[PDB]
Image: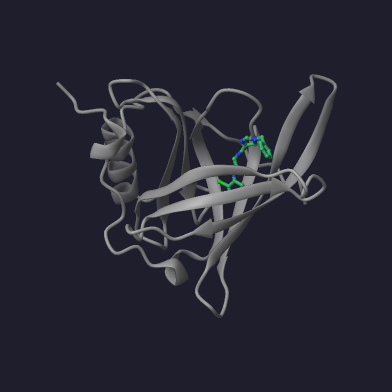
Length: 175
Ligand SMILES: O=C(c1cn(Cc2ccccc2)cn1)N1CCN(c2ccccc2Cl)CC1
């Protein structure tokens, strides 16, 4: 019944880079395959004079049960036809020689309480996503207001990721 094709997904109409800048706290996430930030995930977006968006993400990464590292990462975004859909060239500060490259879609946001982000790394033949990740961001790490809660839940379901998100802890672990 539900249309889960990635090309059918709506994103933030008239997305505004300047308003989106500043600190964002990831409170929930749906994982992709492979190694990935685990928790204490804080993103700091910013827009330079020329108007190109970039961001830094810090977070705990599990190497062993015995060993974690606070991985500082950096991202730089490239605009497309759609102002909510970017191409994020990203990397760890140590491994800056080595870089990854993802879709980065701002699915929805109100700029001052919540944001829903999404990325498809691989399509199935039917157009649905085979490997996706999604962050639920918040300006306040104590939670989202009632209207944000309703919207996030609605968007999570429309991305066909209902009940696939997991809550993320914030402990000042990477301060
Ligand atoms: O946890 C990961 C991650 C790490 N990897 C491994 C990796 C592959 C290729 C290069 C560096 C690291 C894959 N996904 N991500 C979550 C954070 N994301 C990111 C990075 C910088 C700014 C903003 C974001 Cl959302 C990058 C993707």
